[PDB]
Image (cartoon, rainbow over all chains, first blue to last red; front, side, top):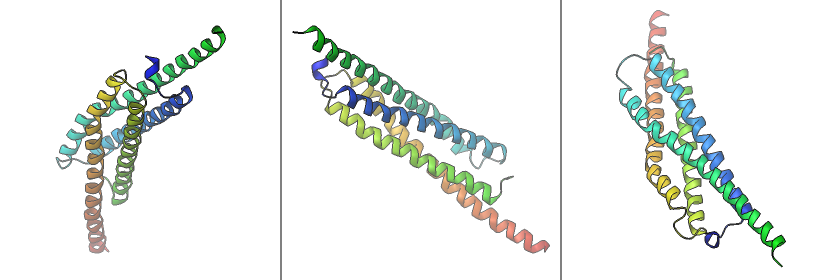
Amino acid sequence: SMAQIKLTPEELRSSAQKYTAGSQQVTEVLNLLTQEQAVIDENWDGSTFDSFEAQFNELSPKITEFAQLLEDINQQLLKVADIIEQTDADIASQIS
Amino acid sequence: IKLTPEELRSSAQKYTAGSQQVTEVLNLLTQEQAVIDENWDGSTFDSFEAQFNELSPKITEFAQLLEDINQQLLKVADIIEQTDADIASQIS
């Protein structure tokens, strides 16, 4: 329902940008450190970081789930923003 | 350990910077989730709100893990640096 949305198309698009920037950063961190984790693993034998590696692997899927949620929110806000903007265009031109 | 103290410290820096960046994103977008909720009445946005809220605690756990890894890498680096100095002194 459009009556419930108190943000303008431009405001929706400003918010959206924060979510996509956020998604990209979280992904950049995850990928960088996923790699660090392997550099360490390869260059360090023993069980001394086994608990860290297991906690990391277990949390990792939560982190990719998060990055994709943020990107999905960006996409939805963008689409809703276009819909509302088009609604204003139509009301202004089709209503006398 | 095939890694020098310097390499360990360079790696540690990445974990702590990553920890901070992940936390900053969570913080910014937690605030933005509240702005949208306050400015979008009804239950339409409830699904995105719910997913975000469920994941939030795990994002916090993840940032804390990165900082813990950072701190241990730094401790290990200190230990190995003393070892390097003792070996060098012994041979010299």
